[PDB]
Image (cartoon, rainbow, N blue to C red; front, top):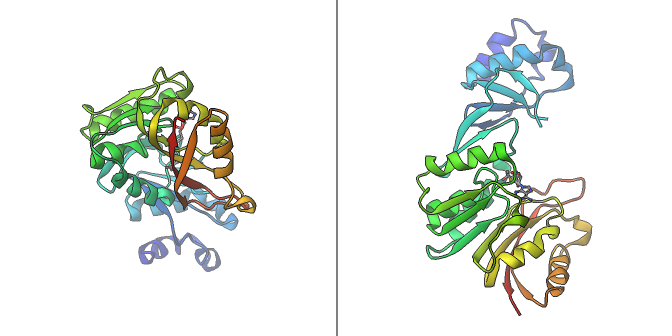
Length: 264
Ligand SMILES: C[S@@+](CC[C@H](N)C(=O)[O-])C[C@H]1O[C@@H](n2cnc3c(N)ncnc32)[C@H](O)[C@@H]1O
C-alpha cells in the first residue's frame, strides 16, 4: 500500500504515469508532505486525495513554504521523542531532517541551569530541555503567530511552571548575565546575534550556536568568525564540539557548534 494506492489510481491513470507515483513522503502529525513528478501535475489533486485516504492524514501539502494539494487544515500536533509539538505545518518550518539535534538537546542540560532560547519557534529545541533536562527556560519568539503555538506547546507538555515565553525580538530582551546555556537555533547570518548572545550569557555559559557555512571554508568557519566577534568584547570562547546537520547544498552546511564563553 502502495498496493491499495496502485489499485485505486491504476483505474484512472495510464500505466506509464502510475509507475511514477510518489514512493516516499514525510508525515508531520496528520499532515503529509508529498513530493510529485512534473508529469503528474495534471492529476495533482486526485493523487493527493488517495494518498490522504490510504495513509490516514487530513491534509496533503506538496513537498517541493508549501502548496496545498488536498484538504484545508494545516494545524496538527506532532509527537517526537515524547514531545508534543503543535504547529501550522504550512507556515512554520519543522523538519525531522533535524530530529537528531532535538534528541541531543534532551540530554545536554542539568536541572539547575537557566536556559535562554533566542529563537524559540514552537519550542523546537527548548521543549526537550524543559521536559528531559528539567532546567528552567526563557523562550523568545519574534513572530506572534508562531508564538501562539510556543505558548500552547508549553501547556501541552506540562512545563508551564519552569518554562516562560516572550513575544519580542531577542535583541530587546532585558536580561543580562542570566544564562547558563543559550540556544541559537537560527541559520540566517546568526553571527549578527552573537553580541546579544554574549550579553545574555553568564561567564562560563554554554552556547549552542547554529549557522550555515559553505564547506569551502570548513573547518575554519563558522568558528573563526564567532571567535573574532567575541574578541570585539574582550571575551574568550572554547569550542567544545562541532556537529554537522542538514548539510543542504548548493555547497553549504548547517552546523551546530557547542561553545563555552568566558567574560574575560
Ligand atoms: C522555528 S526556528 C527553525 C528551526 C528548524 N527549522 C527546525 O526544523 O528545527 C527559527 C525561528 O526564529 C524566530 N526568529 C527569527 N528572528 C528572531 C528574533 N530576532 N528574535 C526572536 N525570534 C526570532 C523565527 O520567528 C522562527 O520562528
